[PDB]
Length: 105
RNA sequence: AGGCUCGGCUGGAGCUUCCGUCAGUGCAGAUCGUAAUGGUAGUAGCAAAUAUUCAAGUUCGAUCCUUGAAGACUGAAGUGG
Image 1 (cartoon, chains in turn green, yellow):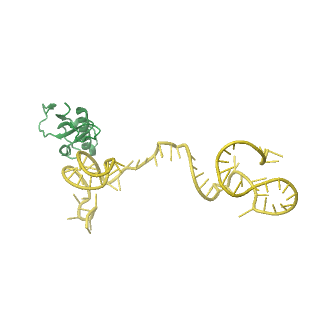
Image 2 (image 1 turned 90 degrees about the vertical axis):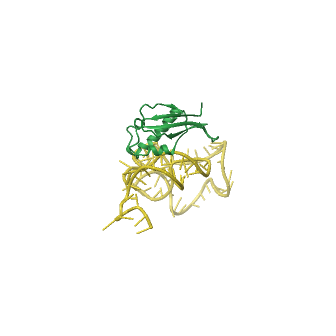
């Protein structure tokens, strides 16, 4: 129940609407972290380097409109951490976003 | 009245009555000299030179140090040697 994995679609276009040109990609990363925090209910969120690569794939200002991610809430192997759970976000390549919903993995 | 005596506390080595006489003898000012301190005030402000992000390392502690990945810039009359 605590260790879980779900596939989500994030509307980065709606999330980062109105942001300045030289902040769109960092703000998209922040919005992905916020989305993972809200959905998986974990304060500790880590973004995979491949997801960062995808978000920055088209430069700093022309961020992709949608992104398909796999949020995997897992146990914190480091026992002295403040919290026992953290979320890891990974990039799911996707060419057609139509009809996709939130999925359990 | 100029000032003075005593009491209490602090301090640790000098001070004092009266008689003569002497003077570098009395400060609120001089945009006075010098030293220190306020309100202003946690205020003005820290805005030129395109730009940083992710993961990890070390550390009591990392936007800023180091490694890797990505994205940009100087653009050879260079931010190079």
